[PDB]
Image (tube, rainbow over all chains, first blue to last red; front, side, top):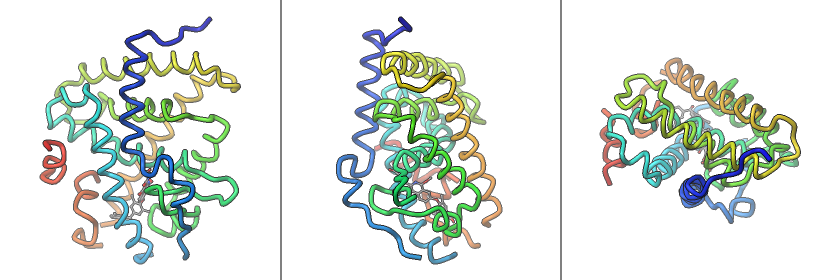
Length: 232
Length: 11
Ligand SMILES: COc1nc(C(=O)NCC(=O)O)c(O)c2ccc(Oc3c(C)cc(C(=O)c4cccc(C)c4)cc3C)cc12
């Protein structure tokens, strides 16, 4: 008897789910198009060459949300800068394979904990892998991942934002529609909603450490891809 | 200064 989605919420769920699926790499063909990376600055090289298409897919995801498009571009810039690494981390974490103990990046590269860490992320690799491991029993479908992405995208607390309250209103829509979908999905996990909100905090911490470490990683800046530098 | 991000947003 917990509330299930309203018609307006079902339309929002369709919109955001479709935006996620259209911009999720090899959605169908990721398990098979996946190749395992063999064996510092050299893994830095394969990880730099793939970051830029990952940022771009996040930009595309945001641009297919009509709520995002009614925001002024300077707010869109702040919002995308705040959430790329959180969304990319989530997108990798839901692609954890317990058998290979790998995450898949860009629907094509399987990396191990050690590879991602030695590769340059440091302790944040442990944070993303441990999120993947704990998301296994969550059984998140495309809709739940899309709604998590929409919730991170629509963060009012981002510094420099103009439409702080318009954004919080958008987020509150996604949060309500997301809880209702969860009530409807009836996962066999106790306190599923409170636990998903803690995963949102886990991703927000990943967002801020990537920021922290980028500061420390400056290694001349022309070595880092342009769009990466834009989204720190 | 967000010039690439700005381009990608306004396309
Ligand atoms: C979040 O997890 C990620 N997810 C995806 C992805 O495709 N997700 C799945 C999906 O979208 O479907 C990536 O492609 C990532 C690429 C690099 C990366 O982590 C880094 C590594 C492994 C090294 C370094 C660096 O050392 C460095 C420093 C300067 C410039 C550059 C590009 C790299 C930086 C990052 C973010 C993290 C990625």
